Amino acid sequence: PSAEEFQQLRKKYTDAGQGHVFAFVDELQTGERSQLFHQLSSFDPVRINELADKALNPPPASLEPLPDIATASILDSDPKDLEQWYEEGLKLVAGNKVAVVLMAGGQGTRLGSSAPKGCFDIGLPSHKSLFQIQAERIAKLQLLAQRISGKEAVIPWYVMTSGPTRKPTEEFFEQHKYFGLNKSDVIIFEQGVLPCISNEGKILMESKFKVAVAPDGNGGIYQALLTSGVREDMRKRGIEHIHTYCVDNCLVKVADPVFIGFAASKQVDIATKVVRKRNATESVGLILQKNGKPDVVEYSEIDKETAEAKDPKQPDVLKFRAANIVNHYYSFKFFESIELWAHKLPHHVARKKIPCIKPNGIKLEQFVFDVFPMTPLEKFACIEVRREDEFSPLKNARGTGEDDPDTSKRDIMSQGQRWIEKAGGIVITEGDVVGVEVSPLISYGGEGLEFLKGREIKAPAFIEK
């Protein structure tokens, strides 16, 4: 950067009310001066002002459960419906019509690690990361699909990272040889980032030569699909169904055929998974009709009477019970519409402790569910699944005793032991350490374990291919 092109950037920033980002330029080495110049060149400060202004200077709801027509349930639907959804979703996989978008754009440090979350080792006997478990679920499902087609089935895995995790994520998959998946079918890409801002919308500085940034929220996924070329790559593959979820769910059923089959059967644009809210006081966001439109409402917005209300058609159960687990389905037609509305997704203010050179700051974030109320009711569906098979988020460092490595480890290992018992394996537990880790290359969802009938397994153990 010449003194001059530099001065132009400074003018742009200064005319935009963000000139303070150059306040320390005098005390910088030239390498540091370049890095600053290049990073500042990648944001439009006028764009930042507009988003900061909307978020800071912005412009009682009726709640009802989604229509019965739009909901199904692993626990409550007819098992014939469930079996048919399963077979139908597997046929879609075998057709090469199913893609996964993994939201791994997040922080991974809450755990004592500055590696991507997905690399985290929960202390399973196998020591596998989240990434590897998930890749193995993909590989086994592809194989399950191959005993239909008699042909290779491919579920491409579009792994959305942010700026900070992109290179460590690439290198992790590299070292693990893509966990036995074809390199062409694992596509790591980036969502956008934004500068973090003060309470007055001024860009925050991480260091004297570097702006503090954050990813633009999990709602940044829609725009990231276009910028990255991901959507057009799906187009070229003839993908028609897209499963999305967050990498922190250690139990995620990747590309779950039931979910795909259910949604495809209703011809929806978006579907969603939930788990059962069992007690009125649990603090979970719910998927429901807010103002006659599909939406997710934070628990703070659910008053006591609504929280406690029982389902009239099913009185043993809560009327509002669809606990959101950030686990979605989309049609490809839906992804083709992204240009028409991605500008309508608002940036929400997350107030945060952001360290910076002189809560104090804001991260601006689009929400993945903000497109739901823009979706016609009849183009939206929701399925309720069993938590103990489907949802175990890794959010806290050890010793918290909630959504942490130990809860995740026990959820997977108790699942392994259940599956083995249902197949007539005898799991013997001699001491506290409970459960058995079943490699997904052996069983995706509990199938394929007949071979264990009668055998005695000492818990803890690891059952691998």
Image (spheres, helix red, strand yellow):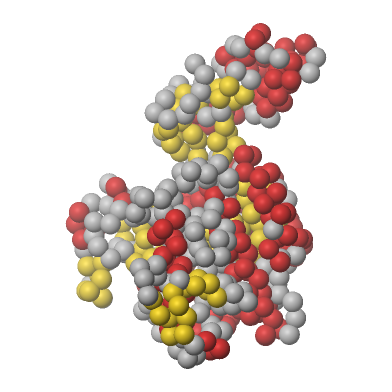
Q: Residue visible at 68% across and 44% down?
A: 167
| Any part of residue 227 in sight | yes
Q: Is residue 435 left or right of residue 211?
A: left
Q: Residue visible at 61% across and 12% down?
A: 24
Q: Quadrant of residue 137?
A: bottom right
Q: Position of residue 225 (x, y in %)?
A: 65, 51
Q: Quadrant of residue 385?
A: bottom left
Q: Position of residue 367 (x, y in %)?
A: 49, 47
Location of residue 406 with respect to 32 vertically, above or below: below
Q: Quadrant of the C terminus?
A: bottom right
Q: Quadrant of residue 190?
A: top right
Q: Residue visible at 43% across and 32% down?
A: 352
Q: Nearer the viewer, residue 90 or 181?
A: 181
Q: Is residue 23 left or right of residue 426?
A: right
Q: Quadrant of the N terminus?
A: top right
Location of residue 449 with respect to 109 vertically, above or below: below
Q: Nearer the viewer, residue 437 or 301?
A: 437
Q: Residue visible at 51% across and 23% down?
A: 356
Q: Position of residue 112 (x, y in %)?
A: 48, 43
Return the residue found at the far bottom.
454
| Any part of residue 240 in sight | no
Q: Nearer the viewer, residue 250 or 203?
A: 250
